[PDB]
Image (cartoon, rainbow, N blue to C red; front, side, top):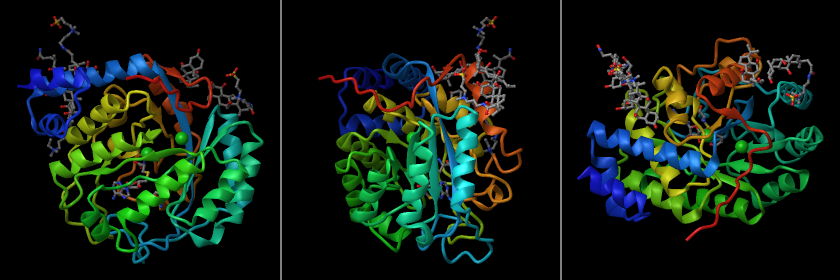
Length: 346
Ligand SMILES: C[C@H](CCC(=O)NCCC[N+](C)(C)CCCS(=O)(=O)[O-])[C@H]1CC[C@H]2[C@@H]3[C@H](O)C[C@@H]4C[C@H](O)CC[C@]4(C)[C@H]3C[C@H](O)[C@]12C
Ligand SMILES: C[C@H](CCC(=O)NCCC[N+](C)(C)CCCS(=O)(=O)[O-])[C@H]1CC[C@H]2[C@@H]3[C@H](O)C[C@@H]4C[C@H](O)CC[C@]4(C)[C@H]3C[C@H](O)[C@]12C
Ligand SMILES: Nc1ncnc2c1ncn2[C@@H]1O[C@H](CSC[C@H](N)C(=O)O)[C@@H](O)[C@H]1O
Ligand code: MET
Ligand SMILES: [Cl-]
Ligand SMILES: [Cl-]
């Protein structure tokens, strides 16, 4: 019974078996109750503020060849770009002028910047009195250390899949063990650290999803980014099935139940597969939103997956749009940098 599973989640009985059954039950009434539980937990622990992280995707150059990603090195049907350090800093300034209190710098694994150009950019943005989050991939400890000394606050490095076999197959340059080592290094260096995974990868099972949830709970991540897999036509996975929105939403809800004081975005991928999908996600456990702040003409060239919603609008439209979203949801914008506010419990 769904009722029994809900009771067990409510009492914090987070066994493998409970999680598996929650993900396996397809009943509408159960799912809606699960979503309501996560929404309530979100409200009680992290409140009504929705934190805005403005993302600048500053280079689509990548040395890796992940099978799912549109930026993989083997994709020749992509115009590659690099923003200059001045462009990046001034674009960050504009986001701060528009009210962003975190700047996220994301790129492919592009050697050109690493480490010192990033450090210089980070230092310049930090003068603006905002949080800086980096999402640059896997690099040596030394690079992560340099970026932390330069002032970076947070680092996003999704674990992608906690199944090491599937991880190696989908990310043939690397391994789950290296991904985890990177995440542990970032935690040690004092970053607020984000992990997370895709849902509906080819070959991924429900037990794999359970393992993702248990992995997240084990390491107590500050942020967890979850979205559906969306096949990209210029990759080896072009003909595979999209991830299911409802199942992905259940993963967000369960993440909030498991990690009640974490920061959890309503990802752009959720809003790509279903119209209004970010808004739904913000009502099922999420409390962060990441408006795209990549300028034209580059924005349209950073498509990890196709259909990305933000590609066609004026490049200053996203921050105002998310502020409207937050209001029509009956929520409030974040007042501070939206760092993790731990609630210690039992
Ligand atoms: C807006 C729609 C449709 C509601 C509706 O239209 N239902 C009939 C009329 C009800 N009214 C009270 C408006 C009038 C009753 C008098 S009447 O004469 O119309 O029957 C309702 C139906 C199911 C609801 C979702 C689920 O819960 C799961 C989840 C819980 C979270 O916490 C918040 C998010 C989420 C996704 C919910 C959002 C929203 O809330 C939904 C879509
Ligand atoms: C960038 C330009 C020119 C002036 C400028 O460079 N302004 C820097 C402001 C810096 N901050 C945001 C940190 C101020 C916070 C003050 S606050 O009192 O909100 O704490 C200013 C002039 C008018 C400002 C918009 C409007 O206002 C409406 C709206 C208010 C929301 O709220 C934030 C979003 C939005 C769209 C604003 C964005 C931006 O800002 C605008 C475009
Ligand atoms: N085809 C793919 N489908 C779905 N996701 C993919 C894909 N390709 C890489 N991603 C994901 O995007 C993450 C970067 S942040 C994405 C952002 N929040 C957004 O939703 O746009 C990577 O770590 C992957 O999990
Ligand atoms: C653009 S994909 C996300 C950033 C980084 N390349 C990573 O795979 O973690
Ligand atoms: Cl962040
Ligand atoms: Cl994310």
